Amino acid sequence: ENRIQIMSTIAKIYRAMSRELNRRLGELNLSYLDFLVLRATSDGPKTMAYLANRYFVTQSAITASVDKLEEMGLVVRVRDREDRRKILIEITEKGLETFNKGIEIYKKLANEVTGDLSEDEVILVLDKISKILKRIEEISQ
Amino acid sequence: ENRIQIMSTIAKIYRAMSRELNRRLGELNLSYLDFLVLRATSDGPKTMAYLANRYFVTQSAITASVDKLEEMGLVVRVRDREDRRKILIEITEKGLETFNKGIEIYKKLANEVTGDLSEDEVILVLDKISKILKRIEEISQ
């Protein structure tokens, strides 16, 4: 039926978007996951545990992504002054500049793919799928 | 803006759905990818190349999934009578029975997550996001 097709179409869109984002972000030396880590840290320091859970990837994938961003000078591992075992991944000035270039790439792509939809149609879809997200996140965890 | 948020929300929905589907399909001894391979072969034999490309996974991931489904007796590798190198992955009677149980699991989950949406609202969203899929697939490949 339709409810099933909505979710199946959402999956197909994600797969295609993921492929194209990896391609376009590659020019910024980033993978789609690397970009997500930057996006996550852009508004405040994040724990590696949060990153893995939020973006549904292994802890090893996060370690690899953070290690990479760290070598690229885009993020830094900050430790508690009293307990250095407490680690937070913080974005750098350069990381924010790269993140912004990435968000613009994402923005350009989003406008292209939703091109057949008017502003109103975009709004109608957004408010509704936001309800779907609320429910699946309640169910999944 | 909104166009960006539509795509970002689509990604979050996919991640949450993927996590829950792996959990619920696990009871059928399948991973989400295993299920996709069964879904793909349910309407006709498929090449391993098609499977990897269609569901954006590595050829190694497909080989592993097919090998697993093969040992579970859900699919079989069929070869051309004249050139055995030409391989097609074909679903079995048991594979179809398991696929149907999987599709019902998917159907039940889809109804839950879209529960806040009326039938009409579901329809409005479907026709519109189908346009987004058409465009990104044209762009991505």
Image: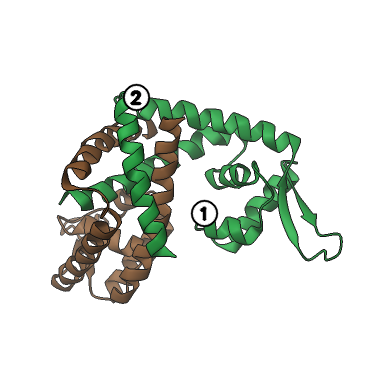
Chain colours: A green, B brown
Determine which residue is flagged by label 1: A55
Q: Chain of mark 2?
A: A
**Residue at position x 35%, y 60% from top?**
B33
Find the distance from the CA under tag 2 to the CA under tag 1. Answer: 28 Å
Where residue A14 appears, as percent x and y from the top left, is 38, 44
Counting from the top left corner in percent of width and height, residue B96 is at 16, 67
Between B135 and A23, which is closer to the camera in this rendering?
Answer: B135
The residue that appears at 27% across and 76% down in the rendered structure is: B72
Q: Which residue is mark 2?
A: A119
Determine the residue positioned at 53% across, 56% down.
A54
Give the image location of residue B139, x and y in percent.
37, 30
The chain ID associated with circle 1 is A
Q: Secondary structure at mark 2?
A: helix
Which numbered tag is attached to residue B14? none
Q: Quadrant of residue A117?
A: top left
For badge 2, the amino acid type reads Glu
